[PDB]
Length: 209
Ligand SMILES: Nc1nc(Cl)c2ncn(Cc3cnc(-c4ccccc4)o3)c2n1
Picture: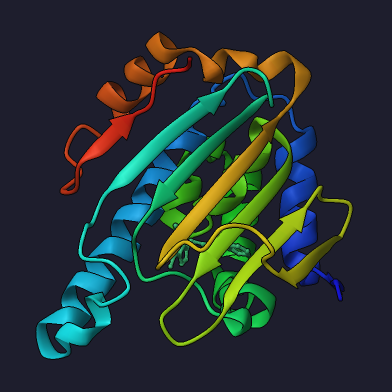
C-alpha cells in the first residue's frame, strides 16, 4: 500500500515559494544535495567507529551523480546512513520547522534563496529544478522505502519494490522541461567544481551511453 501525507504547513509554504518565485540561480540545488550526502556519509562513518557491523550493508562511502536524458532525471546517490520511515514521514520535517520559518523570514528581510542551506532546509531546493522528487532510501535499522512528492501539499511513502540498495539514499530529480541543462556532463562538472570541490568522499559523475 501507498500512504499519503500532508507536509507540515511551513514546509508546504516553503515548497510553494521555491517552486514559484523567480530565481535564476537554480544550480545551487546540486551543492545542497551533495552536502546532505556528505553529512549522511559522515554519520555512518562515525557510527562505524564504535560498531563496525554498521558497514555490513556496504563498506564503500561515495556519492554518484547519474544523469539520464532519456528519463529526464538527475539522480544523486550516496551510501550514507540512509533514512528510516520515521525520518521520511515525520522527523526530518519536524527538525526543519524552525529553519524553514527563519529562512522565509530572512527572505522577507532581503536574504537570497541561495542561503537556503544555511537554514538547514537545502533539500527543498530540489524543487528549483524538479517537478517531482523521488527518494529511495535504506537505513540499517529499517526497510527500503520510496518517498515521492510533486509538491502541492502532499507526499507519499511506500515500501520500495525496486532493487536493493544495501544502505544509503537515491534522490531522483524529475526535471522541469526547461531545466534539462542539469543533465549535461559539462554543466554538472561546472557546478560541482564551483560549489562542492572540497567534499571528503569520492564524487563520480556518470556519463550517459
Ligand atoms: N542524502 C541524505 N541522506 C540522509 Cl540520511 C539525510 N538526512 C537528512 N537529509 C537531508 C534532508 C532533509 N530533509 C530531507 C527529506 C528527504 C526525504 C523526504 C523528506 C525530507 O532530507 C539527508 N540526505
